[PDB]
Amino acid sequence: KSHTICRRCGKRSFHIQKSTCACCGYPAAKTRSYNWGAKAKRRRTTGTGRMSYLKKVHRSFKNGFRSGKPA
Amino acid sequence: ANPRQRNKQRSGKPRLTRRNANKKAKAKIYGNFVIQQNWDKHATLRQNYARLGLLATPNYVTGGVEKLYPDPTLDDVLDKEISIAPAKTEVVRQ
Amino acid sequence: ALKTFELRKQSQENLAEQLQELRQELASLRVQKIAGGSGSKLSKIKTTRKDIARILTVINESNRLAAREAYKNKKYIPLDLRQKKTRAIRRALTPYEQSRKTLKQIKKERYFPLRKYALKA
Amino acid sequence: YVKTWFNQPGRKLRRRQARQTKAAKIAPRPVEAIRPAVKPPTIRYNMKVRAGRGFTLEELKAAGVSRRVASTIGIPVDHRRRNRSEESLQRNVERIKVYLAHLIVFPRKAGQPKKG
RNA sequence: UUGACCUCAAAUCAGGUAGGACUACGCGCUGAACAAUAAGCGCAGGAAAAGAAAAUAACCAUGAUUCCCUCAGUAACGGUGAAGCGGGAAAAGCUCAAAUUUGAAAUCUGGCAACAUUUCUUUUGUUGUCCGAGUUGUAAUUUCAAGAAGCUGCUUUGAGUGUAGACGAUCGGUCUAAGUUCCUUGGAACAGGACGUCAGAGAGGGUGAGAACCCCGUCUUUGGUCGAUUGGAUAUGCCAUAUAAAGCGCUUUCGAAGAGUCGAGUUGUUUGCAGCUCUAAAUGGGUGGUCAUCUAAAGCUAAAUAUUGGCGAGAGACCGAUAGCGAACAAGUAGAGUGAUCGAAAGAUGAAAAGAACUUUGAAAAGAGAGUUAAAUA
RNA sequence: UUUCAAUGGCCCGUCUUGAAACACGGACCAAGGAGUCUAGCAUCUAUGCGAGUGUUUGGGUGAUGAAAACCCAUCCGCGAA
RNA sequence: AGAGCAUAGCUGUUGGGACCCGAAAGAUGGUGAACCAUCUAGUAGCUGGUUC
RNA sequence: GCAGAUCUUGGUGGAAGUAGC
RNA sequence: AAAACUUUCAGCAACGGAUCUCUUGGCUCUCGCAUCGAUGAAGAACGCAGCGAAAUGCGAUACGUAAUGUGAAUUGCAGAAGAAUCAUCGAAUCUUUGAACGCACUGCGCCUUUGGGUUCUACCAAAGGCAUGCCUGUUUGAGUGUCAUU
Ligand SMILES: [Zn+2]
């Protein structure tokens, strides 16, 4: 084989010789994306995962990110 | 259609629906209490300013004006003193 | 299921003493269910997981409240006992320093403020 | 790119709601400031009179309004414009004077220390 | 020598901050082919950018920026293609450097100690003290529109903290008209016929077939009510470091204005910009037609404007399962490819599962007798 | 309708070519499948007004959908010259 | 002794993808001479088709 | 508004129970 | 010439999924709003659902806990009687990765503190920490420095 899993995206695109993922650009900090890959971008953008924290932020904006205990 | 918008369509969680759509309702008046008491909430601000005897614009109006019913020399400009103006309405007198 | 009302009027040591008794009880039911468990065992587990969670909450609630009281009126407090909101909100100018003006500007708004007026038609 | 004007009636409504929003905040004072009367700068238009940006300092001095008071009662000041003739001066001095006649200025509370 | 100052380092020292993601709109840099073009790279916000004239004009002159209409398919150029004026939307102005506070660094961060305050025990400050920063310059004052200093007599004044109520905004509760009468058909009445009711409600949806009156709702509501969090005002109590600070007026006194920039030569990118060589002035310099206008080489700034993304919302002379998004359903899923990437097909029993008990043939799958249903030509 | 009898009847479309010959396309059926939208110009007709004419950049206004309808301040375009 | 101006329709015409299907690409950026994505609906005097 | 585009998608035939395995 | 076979027509049964009807979907337009991340984001992985086809939800407190509200459900089963596979939501929790941060990328560690224990000096386990650039300050020490220095 020529590829293995990736520590960042888990997709089998991590080249062995160069130790560089062909999907997400690992181990570089900036994730690999290209404006001509419109369909590819839609396959991994925001919203394709849990969005666990971002959903919490949207829920908390309505009341102004308030804290404390209700009376 | 977006993966983010499809995600909340496939979820069981409800949307963060905010019922704020209220058109044709005009802003309520604060600031002056005298204006607030005599301000009606249906008429426009032009109609309310005219009814209360005030001027909405000290300049020209860049359009027509509604017609609801059919109608029935430097010395004298510098040394002069204009004698104020009468109050057309009880609000202006107030 | 133990209620949070009477789970909040006892000390932590006995409150933590209720932790492990529920822990082996939950562990014991798992031993019973793998060797044959009725519908009650599934519920008895379901009741006790939430029961463990309820008492774990009041341990963590009281421990934080103890930390909040201890770090009251202190300049620097742990990051856990701080606002979160958003990262940008924590970096924005505070309302106090957004209201700062030079003494030149204070004299402008003191002697020449925007007046409240009206025009007679 | 093709620009479409489907939001044309929605911009009309949005702009009118801003005038109502502005008038709610400043209840009795006009929604616009008084503008001067100037003449356009060409041989094609110098006969017409239109509205300017603000009143000159020489027009405000004659009318009796200082350039610091002027901005506070809704009179814009144009430091750039000047009066090359006496007709422009008198046309806009009278405009300021008429404005002051029709104007009610509500009094402001003033901080007053005990002594000194 | 002690010791100050300047360095150069160190610390798992204290307090901070940057990265990555999104990128519809926005601002830079870069760039081919068939043009600031796609791509590539860099950086933001709720808008961004621009912005208070080194601007137009040649007039009776205009007056920051931005956007729309017009100018105009015009001038000009070699088919490209503006701008001034004009009409609208919106309007708001300002801050430094260059002055000796010199009769008094008047300025600021931090540590510590109290006192407050909160969208908040999470936030944000005040007072006191010590240390540090700072005279190689922190405040007050000044920005050309001026201004300073004197003089003069008129008009002025809070960066304070509570209480009360009113007026607004935001969030969460609560309040709400009238047939399920009679006859017929039907499995079912929501149909037809008769007799009635409500209507500021005859939108829409659900319910066993076309329901204003069965249900949720709709109207009232452009509000009553109960709380919670807030904004700008009003009224009023207290406090107020005013020996102060301003505007206007007057002059036998003064008035600083940004340089490897402007500009010149030359070479490249697309006039602007960039490199390279050279390199200024002080009624000087810029841009225009002797004259007019502006005052660069420092900075900030809401609104009108944009918005295939994000959080919601309301719609439509749109498509109606080979259509409309690739995807109405396990859809960027299954699946394919080493990988980059590629990427489907697939909606409908009935009102109700009442989803065919039971007997029988068969190794079984199934079949036949039955059975349910208005209908198994569901 | 089926079938019989009498008489007649060369496979359709495209291109070619006087014409055909041709060479092409056609196993069959269902569904889909091609002069559209928009900017400018010119002719003609209709409609409105007429030495005039054009409301919709915008403003005013519109409580029963308010993206509609209704109203028109200043310009400007094209004509008259 | 001015006949225009505005709107609608018809027709013709010129641009845009421009009746539809059709011709090797080239360029940019990637993946392991090759492969992939976009520019692209690139370029057609020509081919086939073009519905009562 | 279809009969054609070696049209597109789907279904289905003769060849054929043939070639063959 | 009847049969068979072939052809045509019709009936019934297959085959197929057209048409019709609709539809919690798409598409388009308009309107309101401004809210990611070292306080660990987007994404990826692995786990938890008594069973869930997946899908969704959640994070060892695992289809959630606290609080508030409604007030009696859940449902294909099952399960509890402030119940709910509910809504709101200010409090807690949130596994391994990932800008990903002790070094590495499986493992190997460092310092400190705490504790074990029937094996107590130590060892062991756990916890707390331990990335880089840069800004302000603090502390410490060097200098080939400038002096000061009778
Ligand atoms: Zn990867």
Image: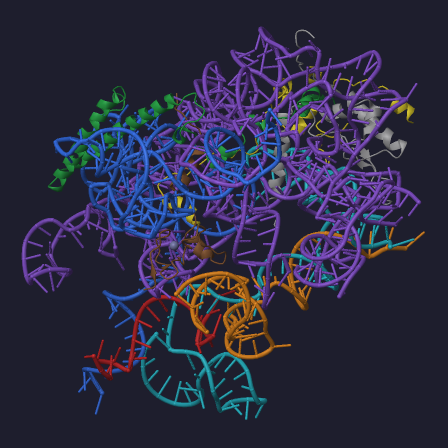
Chain colours: A brown, B yellow, C green, E purple, F cyan, G orange, H red, I blue
Name the side, left or right, on which F33 lies relative to C7: right
Name the side, left or right, on which D77 lies relative to A37: right
Q: Is residue B20 visible?
A: no
Q: Residue at x 83, y 37 (%)?
A: D49
Which corner quadrant of the image does residue F4 belong to? bottom left
Name the side, left or right, on which D70 lies relative to E190: right
Q: Residue at x 70, y 17 (%)?
A: D106
Figure check: E2 above or below E341: above
- The percent position of residue I85, horizontal first and vertical second, equals 28, 36
Which corner quadrant of the image does residue B11 belong to? top left
Q: Quadrant of the C terminus of chain D?
A: top right
- The percent position of residue E98, horizontal first and vertical second, equals 74, 33
The quarter of the image that holds ligand 1 is: bottom left
Give the tally of numbered discs: 0
Figure check: A49 above or below E34: above
- The percent position of residue I97, horizontal first and vertical second, equals 35, 47
Report the front residue among B29 and H21: H21
Figure check: E88 above or below E260: above
Q: Residue at x 72, y 33 (%)?
A: B65
Figure check: E236 above or below C111: above
- The percent position of residue F29, horizontal first and vertical second, equals 38, 70
Report the front residue among E249 and B71: E249
Q: Residue at x 76, y 30 (%)?
A: D77
Report the front residue among E80 and F69: E80
Q: Is residue D80 visible?
A: yes
Q: Quadrant of the N terminus of chain D?
A: bottom right
